[PDB]
Image: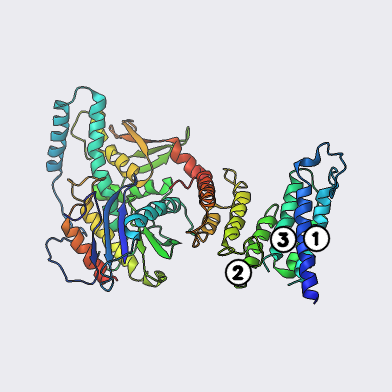
Amino acid sequence: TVGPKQAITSEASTTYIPSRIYSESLLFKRQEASLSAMAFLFQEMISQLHRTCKTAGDFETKLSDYGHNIGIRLLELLNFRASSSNYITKMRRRDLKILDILQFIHGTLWSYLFNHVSDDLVKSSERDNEYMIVDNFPTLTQFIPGENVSCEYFVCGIIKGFLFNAGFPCGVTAHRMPQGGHSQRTVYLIQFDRQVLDREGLRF
Amino acid sequence: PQYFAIIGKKDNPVYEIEFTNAENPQGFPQDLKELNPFILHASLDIVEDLQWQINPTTDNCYLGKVDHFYGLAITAYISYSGMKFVMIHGNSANSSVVIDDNNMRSFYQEVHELYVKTLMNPFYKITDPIRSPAFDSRVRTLARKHL
Amino acid sequence: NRSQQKSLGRQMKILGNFQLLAGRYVDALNSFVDAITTLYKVRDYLWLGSALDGISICFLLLSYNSISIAAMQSPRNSIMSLSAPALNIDVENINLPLLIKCISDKVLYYYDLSLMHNSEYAPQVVYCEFLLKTLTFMTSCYKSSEFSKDVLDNIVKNQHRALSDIPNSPMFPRFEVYFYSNKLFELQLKEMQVEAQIKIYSTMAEVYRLLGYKR
Protein backbone atom coordinates (compact mmCIF):
# COMPACT_ATOMS: atom_id res chain seq x y z
CA THR A 1 0.00 0.00 0.00
CA VAL A 2 2.19 2.82 -1.31
CA GLY A 3 0.97 4.03 -4.68
CA PRO A 4 -2.71 3.78 -5.41
CA LYS A 5 -4.52 5.61 -8.17
CA GLN A 6 -6.06 7.86 -5.52
CA ALA A 7 -3.52 10.13 -3.80
CA ILE A 8 0.12 10.95 -3.14
CA THR A 9 1.88 10.49 0.19
CA SER A 10 4.24 12.99 1.84
CA GLU A 11 7.10 11.60 3.93
CA ALA A 12 10.19 13.48 5.08
CA SER A 13 13.66 13.01 3.65
CA THR A 14 16.66 12.04 5.85
CA THR A 15 14.53 9.87 8.13
CA TYR A 16 15.29 6.39 9.45
CA ILE A 17 16.51 3.60 7.17
CA PRO A 18 13.76 1.01 6.48
CA SER A 19 14.07 -2.80 6.21
CA ARG A 20 15.92 -4.66 3.44
CA ILE A 21 13.84 -7.32 1.69
CA TYR A 22 14.63 -8.24 -1.95
CA SER A 23 17.46 -7.44 -4.36
CA GLU A 24 19.28 -9.00 -7.32
CA SER A 25 22.10 -8.23 -9.76
CA LEU A 26 20.89 -6.80 -13.06
CA LEU A 27 23.99 -7.70 -15.09
CA PHE A 28 23.89 -11.09 -16.78
CA LYS A 29 25.81 -14.06 -15.63
CA ARG A 30 26.57 -16.22 -18.65
CA GLN A 31 23.97 -18.99 -18.71
CA GLU A 32 23.50 -21.65 -21.37
CA ALA A 33 20.76 -24.16 -22.09
CA SER A 34 20.17 -26.79 -24.76
CA LEU A 35 18.44 -25.98 -28.04
CA SER A 36 16.13 -28.98 -27.57
CA ALA A 37 14.42 -27.64 -24.42
CA MET A 38 13.55 -24.28 -25.97
CA ALA A 39 12.46 -26.06 -29.16
CA PHE A 40 10.16 -28.29 -27.08
CA LEU A 41 8.64 -25.25 -25.34
CA PHE A 42 8.26 -23.54 -28.74
CA GLN A 43 6.37 -26.47 -30.27
CA GLU A 44 4.19 -26.71 -27.16
CA MET A 45 3.35 -23.02 -27.66
CA ILE A 46 2.42 -23.60 -31.31
CA SER A 47 0.50 -26.78 -30.38
CA GLN A 48 -1.66 -25.03 -27.76
CA LEU A 49 -2.35 -22.12 -30.11
CA HIS A 50 -3.22 -24.60 -32.86
CA ARG A 51 -5.60 -26.24 -30.37
CA THR A 52 -7.42 -23.14 -29.13
CA CYS A 53 -7.71 -21.05 -32.33
CA LYS A 54 -9.98 -21.37 -35.36
CA THR A 55 -8.27 -19.80 -38.39
CA ALA A 56 -4.81 -18.68 -39.42
CA GLY A 57 -5.04 -14.89 -38.99
CA ASP A 58 -5.88 -14.54 -35.30
CA PHE A 59 -3.44 -17.41 -34.61
CA GLU A 60 -0.76 -15.22 -36.22
CA THR A 61 -1.85 -12.18 -34.18
CA LYS A 62 -1.81 -14.21 -30.95
CA LEU A 63 1.71 -15.45 -31.72
CA SER A 64 2.73 -11.87 -32.51
CA ASP A 65 1.31 -10.77 -29.14
CA TYR A 66 3.38 -13.54 -27.51
CA GLY A 67 6.47 -12.10 -29.20
CA HIS A 68 5.39 -8.55 -28.27
CA ASN A 69 5.43 -9.36 -24.57
CA ILE A 70 9.12 -10.36 -24.79
CA GLY A 71 10.11 -7.39 -26.99
CA ILE A 72 8.68 -4.62 -24.78
CA ARG A 73 10.59 -6.16 -21.87
CA LEU A 74 13.76 -6.77 -23.82
CA LEU A 75 14.35 -3.20 -25.08
CA GLU A 76 15.19 -1.57 -21.73
CA LEU A 77 17.21 -4.55 -20.48
CA LEU A 78 19.49 -4.65 -23.51
CA ASN A 79 19.94 -0.87 -23.67
CA PHE A 80 20.70 -0.65 -19.94
CA ARG A 81 23.18 -3.50 -20.13
CA ALA A 82 24.76 -1.98 -23.24
CA SER A 83 25.12 1.38 -21.49
CA SER A 84 27.43 -0.17 -18.89
CA SER A 85 24.30 -0.64 -12.08
CA ASN A 86 25.74 0.54 -8.75
CA TYR A 87 28.98 0.72 -10.76
CA ILE A 88 29.44 4.11 -12.41
CA THR A 89 27.97 4.16 -15.95
CA LYS A 90 26.10 6.81 -18.02
CA MET A 91 23.54 6.45 -20.89
CA ARG A 92 23.85 5.19 -24.49
CA ARG A 93 22.82 7.20 -27.55
CA ARG A 94 19.10 6.34 -27.21
CA ASP A 95 18.92 6.34 -30.98
CA LEU A 96 16.01 7.93 -32.78
CA LYS A 97 16.53 7.50 -36.52
CA ILE A 98 15.02 4.51 -38.27
CA LEU A 99 18.34 3.41 -39.86
CA ASP A 100 20.15 2.81 -36.51
CA ILE A 101 17.59 0.96 -34.39
CA LEU A 102 17.59 -1.64 -37.17
CA GLN A 103 21.38 -1.56 -36.92
CA PHE A 104 20.94 -2.04 -33.16
CA ILE A 105 18.64 -5.04 -33.77
CA HIS A 106 20.93 -6.66 -36.36
CA GLY A 107 23.99 -6.08 -34.20
CA THR A 108 22.95 -6.66 -30.60
CA LEU A 109 19.48 -8.28 -30.46
CA TRP A 110 20.25 -11.26 -32.69
CA SER A 111 23.63 -11.71 -31.02
CA TYR A 112 21.80 -11.63 -27.69
CA LEU A 113 19.00 -14.03 -28.63
CA PHE A 114 21.39 -16.30 -30.52
CA ASN A 115 25.09 -17.03 -30.59
CA HIS A 116 25.40 -15.61 -34.12
CA VAL A 117 24.90 -12.10 -35.46
CA SER A 118 22.04 -11.46 -37.91
CA ASP A 119 23.04 -11.95 -41.50
CA ASP A 120 21.91 -9.20 -43.88
CA LEU A 121 19.85 -6.01 -43.61
CA VAL A 122 18.83 -4.15 -46.78
CA LYS A 123 16.20 -1.58 -47.75
CA SER A 124 13.62 -1.80 -50.53
CA SER A 125 14.39 -0.14 -53.86
CA GLU A 126 10.82 -0.23 -55.18
CA ARG A 127 9.30 1.69 -52.26
CA ASP A 128 10.34 3.50 -49.12
CA ASN A 129 9.18 2.49 -45.57
CA GLU A 130 9.86 -1.18 -46.45
CA TYR A 131 12.88 -2.73 -44.79
CA MET A 132 14.20 -6.25 -45.22
CA ILE A 133 15.62 -8.14 -42.26
CA VAL A 134 16.89 -11.54 -43.40
CA ASP A 135 18.83 -14.47 -42.02
CA ASN A 136 19.92 -17.66 -43.73
CA PHE A 137 18.82 -20.22 -41.15
CA PRO A 138 16.07 -19.74 -38.52
CA THR A 139 17.11 -21.42 -35.28
CA LEU A 140 13.71 -20.95 -33.65
CA THR A 141 11.83 -23.00 -36.23
CA GLN A 142 14.03 -25.45 -38.09
CA PHE A 143 11.93 -28.41 -36.95
CA ILE A 144 8.69 -27.78 -38.89
CA PRO A 145 8.01 -28.50 -42.63
CA GLY A 146 8.88 -25.42 -44.62
CA GLU A 147 5.62 -24.77 -46.46
CA ASN A 148 4.04 -23.19 -43.36
CA VAL A 149 5.16 -19.64 -42.58
CA SER A 150 2.77 -18.66 -39.73
CA CYS A 151 4.89 -20.41 -37.08
CA GLU A 152 7.65 -17.95 -38.04
CA TYR A 153 5.70 -14.96 -36.78
CA PHE A 154 6.80 -15.21 -33.10
CA VAL A 155 10.27 -13.80 -33.74
CA CYS A 156 8.85 -10.95 -35.82
CA GLY A 157 6.33 -10.57 -33.03
CA ILE A 158 9.44 -9.67 -31.03
CA ILE A 159 10.48 -7.09 -33.65
CA LYS A 160 7.16 -5.21 -33.70
CA GLY A 161 7.29 -5.41 -29.91
CA PHE A 162 10.79 -4.04 -30.11
CA LEU A 163 9.76 -1.20 -32.41
CA PHE A 164 6.31 0.07 -31.32
CA ASN A 165 7.40 0.51 -27.71
CA ALA A 166 10.56 2.32 -28.84
CA GLY A 167 8.57 5.12 -30.48
CA PHE A 168 8.34 3.86 -34.07
CA PRO A 169 4.99 2.11 -34.62
CA CYS A 170 5.00 -0.35 -37.50
CA GLY A 171 3.66 -3.68 -38.69
CA VAL A 172 5.51 -6.85 -39.71
CA THR A 173 4.80 -9.83 -41.94
CA ALA A 174 7.11 -12.71 -42.80
CA HIS A 175 7.58 -14.74 -45.98
CA ARG A 176 10.01 -17.43 -47.13
CA MET A 177 12.14 -16.59 -50.18
CA PRO A 178 14.06 -19.82 -51.08
CA GLN A 179 17.25 -18.26 -52.43
CA GLY A 180 20.47 -20.20 -52.96
CA GLY A 181 21.48 -23.27 -51.00
CA HIS A 182 19.34 -22.24 -48.02
CA SER A 183 15.87 -23.70 -48.59
CA GLN A 184 14.41 -21.67 -45.72
CA ARG A 185 15.61 -18.06 -45.62
CA THR A 186 12.70 -16.24 -43.90
CA VAL A 187 12.42 -12.61 -44.95
CA TYR A 188 10.69 -10.41 -42.38
CA LEU A 189 9.43 -7.17 -43.90
CA ILE A 190 8.52 -4.15 -41.78
CA GLN A 191 5.61 -1.95 -42.86
CA PHE A 192 5.68 1.42 -41.11
CA ASP A 193 2.87 3.97 -41.22
CA ARG A 194 2.85 7.42 -42.77
CA GLN A 195 2.62 9.28 -39.44
CA VAL A 196 6.16 8.36 -38.41
CA LEU A 197 7.70 9.08 -41.85
CA ASP A 198 6.52 12.67 -42.20
CA ARG A 199 7.78 13.09 -38.61
CA GLU A 200 11.23 12.33 -39.97
CA GLY A 201 10.00 14.19 -43.02
CA LEU A 202 9.78 17.17 -40.68
CA ARG A 203 13.31 16.53 -39.36
CA PHE A 204 15.04 17.52 -42.69
CA PRO B 1 10.65 19.51 -0.94
CA GLN B 2 10.42 17.62 -4.26
CA TYR B 3 7.53 15.93 -6.09
CA PHE B 4 8.68 12.88 -8.08
CA ALA B 5 6.80 11.08 -10.83
CA ILE B 6 7.12 8.49 -13.60
CA ILE B 7 4.61 9.02 -16.42
CA GLY B 8 3.42 6.61 -19.09
CA LYS B 9 3.17 7.20 -22.82
CA LYS B 10 -0.63 7.66 -22.79
CA ASP B 11 -0.24 10.39 -20.08
CA ASN B 12 -0.73 8.32 -16.95
CA PRO B 13 1.45 8.00 -13.83
CA VAL B 14 2.87 4.70 -12.66
CA TYR B 15 4.72 6.19 -9.67
CA GLU B 16 4.21 9.34 -7.62
CA ILE B 17 5.92 10.42 -4.36
CA GLU B 18 6.47 13.74 -2.55
CA PHE B 19 9.38 14.08 -0.13
CA THR B 20 10.36 17.06 2.00
CA ASN B 21 13.08 18.31 4.32
CA ALA B 22 12.31 17.60 7.97
CA GLU B 23 12.48 21.27 9.03
CA ASN B 24 9.25 21.91 7.10
CA PRO B 25 7.23 19.00 8.50
CA GLN B 26 4.39 20.05 6.23
CA GLY B 27 5.71 20.62 2.73
CA PHE B 28 4.65 22.64 -0.33
CA PRO B 29 2.15 25.12 1.20
CA GLN B 30 -1.11 24.98 -0.86
CA ASP B 31 0.72 24.11 -4.11
CA LEU B 32 0.57 20.37 -3.38
CA LYS B 33 -3.16 19.86 -3.84
CA GLU B 34 -3.68 21.84 -7.02
CA LEU B 35 -0.60 23.20 -8.75
CA ASN B 36 1.85 20.30 -8.81
CA PRO B 37 -0.13 17.77 -10.91
CA PHE B 38 -1.02 20.47 -13.44
CA ILE B 39 2.45 21.93 -14.02
CA LEU B 40 3.81 18.40 -14.45
CA HIS B 41 1.23 17.71 -17.17
CA ALA B 42 2.22 21.07 -18.66
CA SER B 43 5.89 20.04 -18.70
CA LEU B 44 4.99 16.76 -20.42
CA ASP B 45 4.32 18.85 -23.56
CA ILE B 46 7.83 20.26 -23.78
CA VAL B 47 9.46 16.96 -22.79
CA GLU B 48 7.44 15.44 -25.66
CA ASP B 49 8.79 18.23 -27.88
CA LEU B 50 12.44 17.63 -26.95
CA GLN B 51 12.33 13.82 -27.16
CA TRP B 52 12.61 13.64 -30.96
CA GLN B 53 15.16 16.37 -31.66
CA ILE B 54 18.90 15.81 -32.12
CA ASN B 55 20.71 18.93 -30.84
CA PRO B 56 19.22 20.35 -27.62
CA THR B 57 18.50 23.91 -26.56
CA THR B 58 24.28 14.60 -26.30
CA ASP B 59 23.07 11.06 -25.43
CA ASN B 60 19.35 12.04 -25.09
CA CYS B 61 18.51 9.94 -21.99
CA TYR B 62 19.15 12.71 -19.45
CA LEU B 63 18.39 16.40 -20.05
CA GLY B 64 18.62 19.50 -17.87
CA LYS B 65 16.02 21.65 -16.14
CA VAL B 66 13.34 21.90 -18.76
CA ASP B 67 11.53 25.05 -17.52
CA HIS B 68 11.42 27.46 -14.59
CA PHE B 69 7.95 28.41 -13.48
CA TYR B 70 6.82 30.17 -10.26
CA GLY B 71 10.37 29.69 -9.01
CA LEU B 72 10.18 25.91 -9.42
CA ALA B 73 12.95 24.04 -11.21
CA ILE B 74 11.47 21.14 -13.16
CA THR B 75 13.91 18.39 -14.15
CA ALA B 76 13.22 15.55 -16.55
CA TYR B 77 14.69 12.26 -17.77
CA ILE B 78 13.59 9.99 -20.62
CA SER B 79 13.95 6.22 -20.48
CA TYR B 80 14.47 3.89 -23.42
CA SER B 81 10.89 2.59 -23.50
CA GLY B 82 9.44 6.11 -23.52
CA MET B 83 8.80 6.53 -19.81
CA LYS B 84 9.37 10.03 -18.48
CA PHE B 85 10.88 10.71 -15.06
CA VAL B 86 9.78 14.30 -14.35
CA MET B 87 10.68 15.57 -10.87
CA ILE B 88 10.33 19.17 -9.71
CA HIS B 89 12.30 21.21 -7.19
CA GLY B 90 10.67 23.50 -4.65
CA ASN B 91 11.99 25.89 -1.99
CA SER B 92 10.88 29.12 -0.33
CA ALA B 93 13.61 30.86 -2.37
CA ASN B 94 15.10 30.06 -5.77
CA SER B 95 16.78 26.68 -6.21
CA SER B 96 19.97 25.54 -7.93
CA VAL B 97 19.72 22.17 -9.68
CA VAL B 98 22.59 22.17 -12.22
CA ILE B 99 25.19 21.83 -9.43
CA ASP B 100 23.46 18.57 -8.39
CA ASP B 101 23.80 17.01 -11.90
CA ASN B 102 26.88 15.24 -10.54
CA ASN B 103 24.45 13.50 -8.16
CA MET B 104 20.91 13.69 -9.59
CA ARG B 105 21.91 12.13 -12.93
CA SER B 106 23.17 9.12 -10.97
CA PHE B 107 19.86 9.15 -9.03
CA TYR B 108 17.97 8.92 -12.31
CA GLN B 109 20.36 6.17 -13.45
CA GLU B 110 19.70 3.80 -10.57
CA VAL B 111 15.98 4.60 -10.43
CA HIS B 112 16.05 3.63 -14.13
CA GLU B 113 17.77 0.44 -12.90
CA LEU B 114 14.95 -0.03 -10.38
CA TYR B 115 12.37 0.47 -13.14
CA VAL B 116 14.12 -2.15 -15.30
CA LYS B 117 13.98 -4.50 -12.27
CA THR B 118 10.25 -3.75 -12.08
CA LEU B 119 9.67 -4.28 -15.83
CA MET B 120 11.40 -7.70 -15.99
CA ASN B 121 8.50 -9.24 -14.04
CA PRO B 122 6.35 -11.06 -16.64
CA PHE B 123 3.26 -10.51 -14.48
CA TYR B 124 3.75 -6.73 -14.46
CA LYS B 125 2.45 -5.33 -17.73
CA ILE B 126 2.72 -1.69 -18.74
CA THR B 127 -0.03 0.82 -17.90
CA ASP B 128 -0.10 -0.63 -14.38
CA PRO B 129 0.69 1.40 -11.23
CA ILE B 130 3.78 0.25 -9.40
CA ARG B 131 2.07 -1.02 -6.25
CA SER B 132 5.15 -2.28 -4.40
CA PRO B 133 6.42 -1.12 -0.99
CA ALA B 134 9.92 -2.39 -1.69
CA PHE B 135 10.15 0.12 -4.55
CA ASP B 136 9.15 2.88 -2.09
CA SER B 137 11.85 1.78 0.37
CA ARG B 138 14.58 1.90 -2.27
CA VAL B 139 13.46 5.22 -3.78
CA ARG B 140 13.28 6.97 -0.41
CA THR B 141 16.72 5.64 0.57
CA LEU B 142 17.94 7.00 -2.77
CA ALA B 143 16.14 10.26 -2.00
CA ARG B 144 17.97 10.39 1.34
CA LYS B 145 21.42 9.59 -0.06
CA HIS B 146 21.10 11.83 -3.14
CA LEU B 147 19.68 14.94 -1.45
CA ASN C 1 12.94 75.25 -16.97
CA ARG C 2 13.68 73.60 -20.31
CA SER C 3 12.68 70.23 -18.81
CA GLN C 4 9.05 71.31 -18.28
CA GLN C 5 8.63 72.77 -21.78
CA LYS C 6 10.41 69.74 -23.27
CA SER C 7 8.10 67.38 -21.36
CA LEU C 8 5.05 69.37 -22.50
CA GLY C 9 6.33 69.22 -26.09
CA ARG C 10 6.91 65.47 -25.68
CA GLN C 11 3.35 65.01 -24.36
CA MET C 12 1.99 67.06 -27.27
CA LYS C 13 4.18 65.03 -29.65
CA ILE C 14 2.80 61.75 -28.27
CA LEU C 15 -0.74 63.16 -28.53
CA GLY C 16 0.00 64.26 -32.11
CA ASN C 17 1.39 60.79 -32.91
CA PHE C 18 -1.67 59.02 -31.44
CA GLN C 19 -4.10 61.43 -33.13
CA LEU C 20 -2.41 61.37 -36.55
CA LEU C 21 -2.15 57.58 -36.39
CA ALA C 22 -5.83 57.59 -35.43
CA GLY C 23 -6.47 60.07 -38.28
CA ARG C 24 -5.55 57.46 -40.92
CA TYR C 25 -8.35 55.07 -39.93
CA VAL C 26 -10.87 53.18 -42.13
CA ASP C 27 -8.66 53.75 -45.26
CA ALA C 28 -10.24 57.23 -46.01
CA LEU C 29 -12.50 55.80 -48.73
CA ASN C 30 -14.58 58.79 -49.98
CA SER C 31 -13.73 61.08 -47.08
CA PHE C 32 -13.95 64.36 -49.04
CA VAL C 33 -15.65 66.33 -46.20
CA ASP C 34 -14.51 69.51 -44.41
CA ALA C 35 -11.98 67.42 -42.37
CA ILE C 36 -11.53 69.45 -39.18
CA THR C 37 -8.09 68.72 -37.62
CA THR C 38 -7.47 66.08 -40.31
CA LEU C 39 -6.26 65.76 -43.90
CA TYR C 40 -8.55 62.89 -45.09
CA LYS C 41 -6.62 62.05 -48.28
CA VAL C 42 -5.25 58.85 -49.81
CA ARG C 43 -1.99 58.68 -47.83
CA ASP C 44 -1.57 62.11 -46.20
CA TYR C 45 -2.46 61.23 -42.59
CA LEU C 46 -0.12 58.22 -42.65
CA TRP C 47 2.71 60.50 -43.81
CA LEU C 48 1.80 63.12 -41.19
CA GLY C 49 1.72 60.30 -38.62
CA SER C 50 5.21 59.29 -39.78
CA ALA C 51 6.46 62.89 -39.47
CA LEU C 52 4.89 63.24 -36.01
CA ASP C 53 6.42 59.88 -35.05
CA GLY C 54 9.87 61.06 -36.18
CA ILE C 55 9.46 64.33 -34.24
CA SER C 56 8.19 62.45 -31.16
CA ILE C 57 11.10 59.99 -31.34
CA CYS C 58 13.55 62.90 -31.69
CA PHE C 59 11.99 64.71 -28.72
CA LEU C 60 11.92 61.55 -26.57
CA LEU C 61 15.55 60.79 -27.46
CA LEU C 62 16.42 64.41 -26.62
CA SER C 63 14.59 64.02 -23.28
CA TYR C 64 16.74 61.03 -22.24
CA ASN C 65 10.49 57.81 -18.84
CA SER C 66 7.62 55.50 -19.77
CA ILE C 67 6.54 57.84 -22.60
CA SER C 68 9.86 57.35 -24.46
CA ILE C 69 9.18 53.92 -25.94
CA ALA C 70 5.55 54.69 -26.83
CA ALA C 71 6.69 56.58 -29.93
CA MET C 72 9.14 53.76 -30.73
CA GLN C 73 6.19 51.36 -30.66
CA SER C 74 4.09 53.87 -32.63
CA PRO C 75 6.68 54.10 -35.43
CA ARG C 76 6.40 50.34 -36.00
CA ASN C 77 2.61 50.65 -35.66
CA SER C 78 2.61 53.37 -38.34
CA ILE C 79 4.86 51.24 -40.58
CA MET C 80 2.61 48.18 -40.18
CA SER C 81 -0.64 50.14 -40.60
CA LEU C 82 0.71 51.77 -43.75
CA SER C 83 1.95 48.34 -44.87
CA ALA C 84 -1.59 46.98 -44.64
CA PRO C 85 -2.04 49.21 -47.69
CA ALA C 86 0.84 50.09 -50.03
CA LEU C 87 3.85 51.63 -48.29
CA ASN C 88 7.45 52.53 -49.15
CA ILE C 89 8.55 54.27 -45.94
CA ASP C 90 12.27 53.48 -46.18
CA VAL C 91 13.24 57.04 -45.17
CA GLU C 92 11.22 56.75 -41.95
CA ASN C 93 12.72 53.27 -41.50
CA ILE C 94 16.20 54.80 -41.84
CA ASN C 95 15.29 57.55 -39.35
CA LEU C 96 14.00 54.93 -36.90
CA PRO C 97 17.14 52.83 -37.44
CA LEU C 98 19.33 55.90 -36.83
CA LEU C 99 17.48 56.87 -33.63
CA ILE C 100 17.36 53.27 -32.41
CA LYS C 101 21.08 52.81 -33.09
CA CYS C 102 21.83 56.08 -31.31
CA ILE C 103 19.84 55.11 -28.21
CA SER C 104 19.62 51.30 -28.26
CA ASP C 105 21.38 48.64 -30.37
CA LYS C 106 19.45 47.39 -33.40
CA VAL C 107 21.78 44.66 -34.85
CA LEU C 108 19.07 43.30 -37.19
CA TYR C 109 18.50 43.39 -40.95
CA TYR C 110 15.54 41.02 -41.44
CA TYR C 111 12.17 41.65 -43.05
CA ASP C 112 9.40 42.28 -40.45
CA LEU C 113 11.67 41.31 -37.53
CA SER C 114 12.84 44.89 -36.92
CA LEU C 115 9.40 45.68 -35.45
CA MET C 116 9.75 42.75 -33.03
CA HIS C 117 13.27 43.89 -32.10
CA ASN C 118 11.92 47.43 -31.61
CA SER C 119 9.15 46.14 -29.33
CA GLU C 120 11.66 44.03 -27.36
CA TYR C 121 13.78 47.16 -26.94
CA ALA C 122 10.63 49.15 -26.10
CA PRO C 123 9.81 46.91 -23.14
CA GLN C 124 13.21 47.77 -21.61
CA VAL C 125 12.41 51.48 -21.19
CA VAL C 126 9.37 50.72 -19.02
CA TYR C 127 11.42 48.00 -17.29
CA CYS C 128 14.10 50.57 -16.41
CA GLU C 129 11.63 53.31 -15.46
CA PHE C 130 9.55 51.01 -13.21
CA LEU C 131 11.60 52.11 -10.17
CA LEU C 132 10.21 55.65 -10.17
CA LYS C 133 7.10 57.54 -9.07
CA THR C 134 4.19 55.12 -9.37
CA LEU C 135 1.51 57.62 -10.45
CA THR C 136 2.24 60.25 -13.09
CA PHE C 137 -1.16 60.69 -14.75
CA MET C 138 -4.56 61.43 -13.20
CA THR C 139 -6.65 58.67 -14.84
CA SER C 140 -4.60 56.12 -12.84
CA CYS C 141 -4.14 58.29 -9.74
CA TYR C 142 -5.63 55.65 -7.40
CA LYS C 143 -4.11 52.66 -9.22
CA SER C 144 -1.65 50.04 -7.95
CA SER C 145 1.10 49.70 -10.57
CA GLU C 146 1.94 50.18 -14.25
CA PHE C 147 1.70 46.38 -14.61
CA SER C 148 -1.90 46.90 -15.84
CA LYS C 149 -0.52 48.13 -19.19
CA ASP C 150 2.82 46.30 -18.95
CA VAL C 151 0.87 43.10 -19.60
CA LEU C 152 -0.91 44.74 -22.58
CA ASP C 153 2.51 45.57 -24.08
CA ASN C 154 3.74 41.99 -24.39
CA ILE C 155 0.29 40.57 -25.26
CA VAL C 156 0.05 42.94 -28.25
CA LYS C 157 3.64 41.82 -29.02
CA ASN C 158 2.54 38.15 -28.91
CA GLN C 159 -0.60 38.88 -30.98
CA HIS C 160 1.39 40.70 -33.65
CA ARG C 161 4.22 38.14 -33.67
CA ALA C 162 2.58 34.69 -33.35
CA LEU C 163 0.67 35.08 -36.63
CA SER C 164 4.02 35.27 -38.47
CA ASP C 165 4.53 31.57 -37.68
CA ILE C 166 2.09 30.01 -40.15
CA PRO C 167 2.37 26.15 -39.79
CA ASN C 168 5.37 24.91 -42.23
CA SER C 169 9.02 23.52 -42.34
CA PRO C 170 10.80 26.95 -42.74
CA MET C 171 9.46 28.94 -39.76
CA PHE C 172 10.71 32.57 -39.42
CA PRO C 173 9.99 32.46 -35.62
CA ARG C 174 10.97 29.29 -33.66
CA PHE C 175 8.39 27.92 -31.15
CA GLU C 176 10.98 27.53 -28.29
CA VAL C 177 12.02 31.21 -27.92
CA TYR C 178 8.46 32.54 -27.88
CA PHE C 179 7.40 29.80 -25.49
CA TYR C 180 10.27 30.84 -23.22
CA SER C 181 9.29 34.49 -23.66
CA ASN C 182 5.84 33.45 -22.46
CA LYS C 183 7.67 31.71 -19.59
CA LEU C 184 8.69 34.98 -17.87
CA PHE C 185 5.25 36.45 -18.59
CA GLU C 186 3.75 35.08 -15.37
CA LEU C 187 4.23 38.00 -12.98
CA GLN C 188 2.19 38.79 -9.80
CA LEU C 189 -1.09 38.99 -11.74
CA LYS C 190 -3.51 38.02 -8.92
CA GLU C 191 -5.62 41.15 -8.38
CA MET C 192 -6.78 42.73 -11.67
CA GLN C 193 -10.20 43.17 -13.32
CA VAL C 194 -11.84 39.90 -14.32
CA GLU C 195 -12.51 40.93 -17.94
CA ALA C 196 -8.79 41.63 -18.35
CA GLN C 197 -7.88 38.20 -16.97
CA ILE C 198 -10.41 36.26 -19.08
CA LYS C 199 -9.19 38.08 -22.21
CA ILE C 200 -5.48 37.67 -21.42
CA TYR C 201 -5.79 33.96 -20.63
CA SER C 202 -7.90 33.61 -23.78
CA THR C 203 -4.95 35.08 -25.70
CA MET C 204 -2.57 32.59 -24.04
CA ALA C 205 -5.02 29.80 -24.94
CA GLU C 206 -5.17 31.13 -28.52
CA VAL C 207 -1.38 31.21 -28.96
CA TYR C 208 -1.00 27.77 -27.35
CA ARG C 209 -3.70 26.23 -29.57
CA LEU C 210 -2.15 27.78 -32.69
CA LEU C 211 1.28 26.60 -31.53
CA GLY C 212 0.00 23.07 -30.85
CA TYR C 213 1.16 23.24 -27.22
CA LYS C 214 -2.04 21.58 -26.09
CA ARG C 215 -1.40 20.83 -22.42
Q: Quadrant of residue A1?
A: bottom left
Q: Residue at x 49, y 62 (%)?
A: C188
Residue that sits furthest to the top in the current view: A54
The amino acid type of the residue labelled 2 equals: Thr
Q: Give the Cα separation between the discs numbered 2 and 1.
A: 28 Å
Q: Is residue A178 visible?
A: yes
Residue A66 versus residue C125 in the image, above or below: above
Q: Callout 3: residue from which chain?
A: C
Tag shown at residue C72: 3
Determine whether the residue tagged by mark 3 lies in a helix, strand or loop. Answer: helix
Residue occupied by mark 1: C54
* Closest to the observer, B45 or A34: B45
Residue occupied by mark 2: C134
Q: Residue at x 82, y 49 (%)?
A: C45
x, y percent for residue A131: 40, 38
The amino acid type of the residue labelled 3 equals: Met
Q: Nearer the viewer, mark 2 or mark 1?
A: 2
Going by the image, does C84 lie left or right of C174? right
Q: Residue at x 73, y 69 (%)?
A: C103
x, y percent for residue A150: 25, 29
> Closer to the N terminus: mark 3 or mark 1?
1
Tags 2 and 1 in contact by the CB under 8 Å rule? no
The amino acid type of the residue labelled 1 equals: Gly
Q: Nearer the viewer, mark 2 or mark 3?
A: 2
> Closer to the N terminus: mark 2 or mark 3?
3
x, y percent for residue B81: 32, 50
* Closest to the observer, A160 or B74: B74
Determine whether the residue tagged by mark 2 lies in a helix, strand or loop. Answer: loop
* Closest to the observer, C153 or A116: C153
Q: Give the Cα separation between the discs numbered 2 and 3.
A: 22 Å
